[PDB]
Image (cartoon, rainbow, N blue to C red; front, side, top):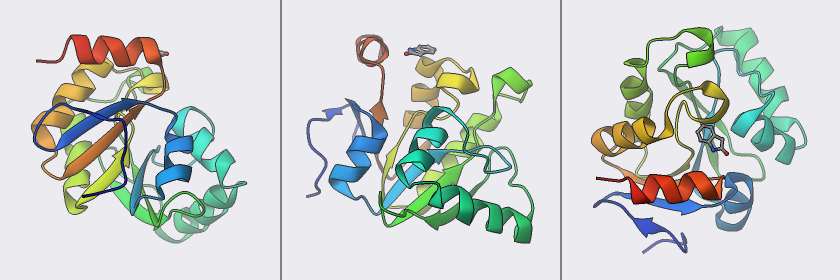
Length: 167
Ligand SMILES: O=C1Cc2ccccc2N1
């Protein structure tokens, strides 16, 4: 049993809810929250900007030190950093950004990072300002992630379309 409430069950392991991931993280304090990161861990907008704002910029400060030591992530890659006030850990995952011309086949590699964690609160990778089709992102998620994933979808309209169209 876990703390996640109000989710619709899509599969054995994937759950979905219309929710602000920031407000959900604050309520649940999950072991892992996933950030929709870029390779530079520059948390300007989208999910990353919202998560970082909720940490009062402490996520960005920590991220800048990580990049200064390790250099950029790979598209499809990830790193584990602090969850600050939102979670125990933040898994920063880089999905391909279609608005930069990245290979959408890298979305499966991105989701494979989730399998290193038994339970996660996450957004749909490469959705929103990353430019991918969220319906496709949900399909790759279900077909790739084997661990227990709780997806937060900010937009109610999109949430209802994801559920109604789910095979
Ligand atoms: O609110 C939103 C923003 C967006 C981008 C692409 C597809 C669906 C949606 N819903």
